[PDB]
Image 1 (tube, rainbow over the protein chains, first blue to last red):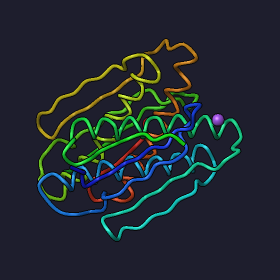
Image 2: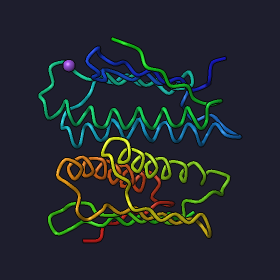
Image 3: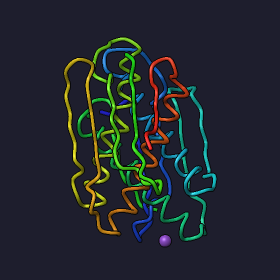
Amino acid sequence: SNAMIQAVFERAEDGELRSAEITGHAESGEYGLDVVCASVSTLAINFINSIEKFAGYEPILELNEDEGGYLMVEIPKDLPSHQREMTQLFFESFFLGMANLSENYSEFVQTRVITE
Amino acid sequence: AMIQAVFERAEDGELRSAEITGHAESGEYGLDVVCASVSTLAINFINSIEKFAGYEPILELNEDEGGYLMVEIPKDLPSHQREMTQLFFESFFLGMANLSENYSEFVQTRVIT
Ligand code: NA
């Protein structure tokens, strides 16, 4: 079956992380889900906030809390090297966080990588 | 659930440690959502250092009486590991600072310098 929270990370053939699409993480009540949603949301929001503060640009974003939550973050093409490298560092940390949530709370979150 | 976070900065601005108290479950109950957010930031910080920077930070964990976590960076880090550590640590601080704004009734974040 499919978990409530779905997280797909897109990687280029050279390993560069291009985007993350997360669904199902909007705030939705009890026995287990709320705390996992909070953890996913914290990682996702801090990822974006860290890019904006430290890398110094705004990524491409699509958001909606409506049908259980939707977040798509996409890295602009042709970023200068320092922005690329900081973004990749944070993106790898975000992926690790989600991968570890999917390992330890596997009935709530699934995390996958796709190629570009 | 009064969560207190204190981050230590050296004279040049480098982050050296964070100490967090009050984030233990429970609960159950509104507060555990805030605790889970704080724990996620702390644990991902630690895991990121270990995976990407290639060393173990110094860590003290006590689950008792509201919970206690202290993470400290080794003093003599080679330059490759030092810079990467700082980006992760700044991100960790930003997350906690933003949590303290969004959940200002439950989380307080400070810096000691
Ligand atoms: Na590339």
